[PDB]
Image: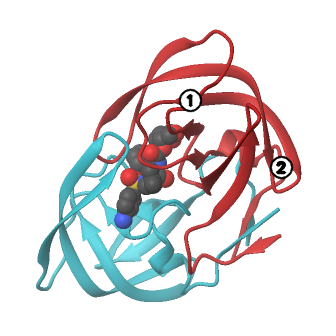
Chain colours: A red, B cyan
Amino acid sequence: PQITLWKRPLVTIKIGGQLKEALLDTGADDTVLEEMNLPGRWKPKMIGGIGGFIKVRQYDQILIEICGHKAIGTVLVGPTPVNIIGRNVMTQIGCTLNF
Amino acid sequence: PQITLWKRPLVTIKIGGQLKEALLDTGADDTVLEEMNLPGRWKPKMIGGIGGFIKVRQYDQILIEICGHKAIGTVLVGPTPVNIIGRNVMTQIGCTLNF
Ligand SMILES: CC(C)CN(C[C@@H](O)[C@H](Cc1ccccc1)NC(=O)O[C@H]1CO[C@H]2OCC[C@H]21)S(=O)(=O)c1ccc(N)cc1
């Protein structure tokens, strides 16, 4: 779909059999989700924002479904205030910016 | 133009007579710029993100020029690691997400 930006660009994702709302974030390099129940192994990692860093668990090769599209890639799980879909996923569903 | 997301959606902006590189950030409600010399009055404000919060100076009715397109609105200045063009400006230049 085409999405204007007068509101936050929220989309419904399905990941690990769970339904969540996440922000389409062109300013995010990778995908970060609030604390969630994901299966498998993971390697620690820290990511920085506008206020500093957070420590997260990096899961590899995780299936995400967004508004009918499917993507596999790295998902970071940690104390983010909001679920964010980063560029690593949006490239796989063909998301573009247009002005 | 149309912008894929395989790399950071960086653009060049003209503000306060200065040229700067900024990241088009659909995940940012407000525009936040690194420390820079801006004229006018302002009000203190704090904004939050990944890792915590930061103190910024809130400038209102500030002119921004991106790819010729002109916008006017609130510009926050403070210790952000990256210049961010938020939804408050992208809406004025007709920016949309498309997938
Ligand atoms: C977390 C969002 C709800 C809000 N953020 C916008 C977001 O795009 C930031 C904007 C951003 C971009 C670069 C550096 C700091 C902040 N990017 C970010 O945190 O991404 C991190 C996760 O993947 C990595 O990608 C880059 C940093 C990592 S934010 O920077 O904190 C922000 C919050 C409020 C306003 N008014 C303006 C900006």
Where disc 1 sits, the SS reads: strand
Type of the residue with mark 2: Ile
Left or right, residue A80 beside residue B60 = right
Measured along the vertical axis of the image, is residue A3 above or below residue B28?
Answer: below
x, y percent for residue B80: 29, 52
Q: Residues within 10 Å of mark 2 (few under 14, many from 20)?
A: some
Q: Residue at x 46, y 63 (%)?
A: B28
Q: Residue at x 33, y 48 (%)?
A: A50
**Image vertical order of residue A65 relative to residue A54, above or below:** below
Which residue is at a point 52% across and 60% down the rendered structure image? B25
Query: Could you tell me which chain the residue with mark 2 belongs to?
Result: A
Q: CA distance from mark 2 to mark 1?
A: 19 Å
Label 1 beta carbon within 8 A of ligand 1: yes
Q: Position of residue A28 (x, y in %)?
A: 55, 46
Question: Above or below — where is A2 with respect to B99?
Answer: below
Q: Quadrant of the N terminus of chain A?
A: bottom right
Pointer 2 or 1: first along the chain: 1
Q: Is residue B44 left or right of residue B80?
A: left
Measured along the vertical axis of the image, is residue A43 above or below residue A32? Answer: above
What residue is shown with label 2?
A93
Provide the residue designation for mark 1: A76
User: Numbered disc 1: what chain?
Assistant: A
- In the rendered image, the quadrant that contains the C terminus of chain A is bottom right
Mark 2: secondary structure: loop
Q: Residues within 10 Å of mark 1 (few under 14, many from 20)?
A: many
Relative depth, front residue between B54 and B80: B54
